[PDB]
Image 1: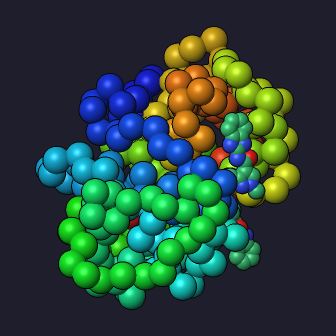
Image 2: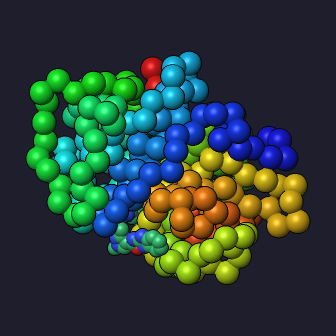
Length: 215
Ligand SMILES: O=C(Nc1nc2ccccc2[nH]1)c1c[nH]nc1-c1ccc(F)cc1
Ligand SMILES: Cc1nn(C)cc1C(=O)Nc1nc2ccccc2[nH]1
């Protein structure tokens, strides 16, 4: 692996989104990861549908919480692999209300065929990420409300409560760090993003890393 990676600069990452008040940090992580994989497959970067998962993924509990791997498993095994575009199934649960499931011909933004889990190794994840693109990970965002910007180093690492998207790292800097895409708009943190120290398992980042697999 290289000294640094940033998939935004390779134009492979969609704009930062806003989950509003809904525990759907997963849907955003899982989907965010798929948006990138679809692009890196050779296709146009399409903004995909988080609402699809909140409403339809029954394995996951909609708004009160979910898990990225269940999404990938659900999409492939219950939804025939289909991920809808956002224009055809837009986010509604911003305020907490999650509509019912639908099928009046939504548009399929991407078709995935599986997913893979990565080891609990920050270095190995970086190895995969550098080659294959943004990785979906779970973290302990207890210490994230207070976040203004900078390389975070004293992150509470006890409870996985939040789902996000790794878009690259930087092993060259004074303090090596992961670059993480977050679903709390762009006012939060560094234009929507956040940098946590790479190597010491900040925020329990290496604990639940996975990525969808296209084609
Ligand atoms: O509730 C969430 N996750 C969760 N915990 C569970 C315990 C028992 C059964 C199902 C469960 N699902 C959740 C809400 N917002 N974000 C996440 C999230 C937390 C961890 C994670 F890895 C991914 C998402
Ligand atoms: C959503 C959600 N569900 N639960 C249980 C907590 C949250 C949450 O913290 N949202 C949130 N915090 C923010 C802090 C700063 C800016 C924007 C912010 N948005």
